[PDB]
Amino acid sequence: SRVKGVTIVKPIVYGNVARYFGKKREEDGHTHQWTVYVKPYRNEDMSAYVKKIQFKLHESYGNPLRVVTKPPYEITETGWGEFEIIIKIFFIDPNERPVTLYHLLKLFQSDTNAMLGKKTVVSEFYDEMIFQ
Amino acid sequence: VTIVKPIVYGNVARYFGKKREEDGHTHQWTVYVKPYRNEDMSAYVKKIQFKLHESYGNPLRVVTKPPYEITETGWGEFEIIIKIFFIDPNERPVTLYHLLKLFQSDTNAMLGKKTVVSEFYDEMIF
Amino acid sequence: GVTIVKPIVYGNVARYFGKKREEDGHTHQWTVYVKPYRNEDMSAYVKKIQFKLHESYGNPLRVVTKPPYEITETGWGEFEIIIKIFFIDPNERPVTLYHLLKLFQSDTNAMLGKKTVVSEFYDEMIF
Amino acid sequence: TIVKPIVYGNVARYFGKKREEDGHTHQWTVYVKPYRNEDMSAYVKKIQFKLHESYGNPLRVVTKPPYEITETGWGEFEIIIKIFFIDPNERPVTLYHLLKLFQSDTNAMLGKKTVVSEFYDEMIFQ
């Protein structure tokens, strides 16, 4: 006897891409450039149903609570260590509890890929968001 | 017999590599209508018009012969209304709207992609 | 009659390592896939999807039941993957698609700066 | 009553020098590919690209995708593409293509390094 609406499912990908500079940036000792991101599994404007996404970077980043309101939902920074990003998705239709994803930022590649195409690391994962 | 005909539409764009100083243009793009499957549209489509932004000279571009597409160059993103007129005058024309997409995500920039694509699928029902 | 239409894409992508990997000879990494065209839950209508990979692989009759309906491997040569699409509805007979796994880029796309082999083909599935 | 749209053209790139060994200054690739990707090899028996007489083996035949031919040379000329069908009755379609190698002047200011000359067409059946 629950009064439910229509079940609505939205498939998403999220993760990070990273690329090594070549040399230890002398000023901060940084080494990689990277973008963490959330994007639809197939091209569509998520802004129909996503108000904002926030990525909580590491405590060592200035302005660590980064937020994005309009697509692409991505944050680009540079760094030297791997750490755990906490990505919260905020829906438009309130009475829709946010979704929270933990993504371990990957910067270095596997020795297996040190032997094949060792340039650009990618770490992406599939998940789906439910509605109504 | 309710006959459906499926289509994709949208645009593709590519970065100059450097803003041209004559007109501050940074991209060339192409906006299009294509059939979902490699079939012929001309059998049932009189013309398609792509109403561009008023910044463009002659903003009402009309395509009557396939391929139903328009190639321009640009500095900015904007909405493109798309009017599909059918060959028997009875059939009501279908208006599609498309937000020209010109600027690459840092993600796709880091993956070394070279072409920005936003494309969409529809069904014209008869 | 039901008469529902669900556009899908299938095919594979491929991105050549840079060099022959000294361990198993592998030169390319690839992903053969079947995706809805729109962003939607296709497990609403798809029970499972079988991918028949070349006999040289292991468990070559790969079967995916939860989206994404993607297989990822490495290899060094091309072959033909037979894709069988099993539906939720029992009255709906499975579809079988053939796809030639493209690993080698063509001269046209090589000369354009293209960095990934993409071979994508289209279909519409009816109910 | 089947119509099949195709794209045909060439890409070329100035190689960077006048190769002194044989004079050849560009490398090009002429191709034919369906407007919307399908197994063209289901109904195309072979595709011919007849080229300038200076090229030994001037009739080149391709029989399976990618339907392209790659070469090097110094000058532009007309490539005759002939498309032969699996169905013995359907007669060969013949396309003419001005192979392009040198760039325009607004596309230099664009930030282009590769040339693209590409045309739509429709193979028609009964």
Image (cartoon, coloured by chain):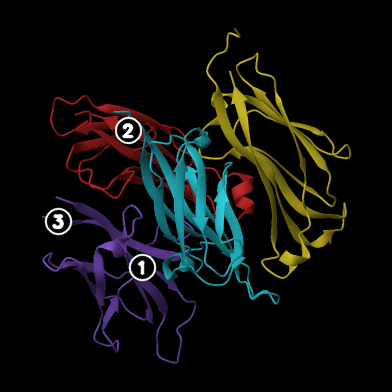
Chain colours: A yellow, B red, C cyan, D purple
* CA separation in Å, label 1 and label 3: 21 Å
Identify the amino acid type marked 3: Phe
- Examine the image and state in which quarter residue B42 appears: top left
Q: CB atoms at circles 3 and 2 under 8 Å apart? A: no
In the figure, C116 relative to A89: above or below? below
Image coordinates of residue A67 in percent, x first then y, are: 72, 30
Q: Nearer the viewer, residue A117 or D116?
A: A117
Q: Residue B54 in the image: x percent, y percent?
A: 37, 31
Instruction: Please tell me which of labels 1 and 3 falls first in the chain.
Output: 1
Quarter containing the C terminus of chain D: bottom left
- Judged from this view, the residue extending furthest toward the front is C90
Can residue D50 be seen here? yes
| Relative side of B38 to C33, left or right | left
C15, above or below C19, in the image: above
Q: Position of residue C118 (x, y in %)?
A: 48, 58
Kind of residue sitting beneath label 1:
Pro
Would you name the residue on which mark 3 appears? D125
Q: Chain of mark 1?
A: D
Which corner quadrant of the image does residue B124 belong to? top left
Q: Residue at x 69, y 63 (%)?
A: A119
- Inspect the image, locate mark 2, and give the three-letter code of the amino acid beneath it: Glu
Query: Residue at 30% across / 86% down in the picture?
Result: D55
Residue indicated by mark 2: B123
Mark 1 crowdedness (10 Å alpha carbons): few <14, some 14-19, many ≥20: some
Question: As displayed, is residue C78 above or below residue A81?
Answer: below
Parent chain of label 2: B
Q: Describe the element under mark 1 as helix, strand or loop.
A: loop
Q: Is residue A87 above or below residue C11?
A: above
Residue D65 badge: 1
Q: Nearer the viewer, residue A82 or C79?
A: C79
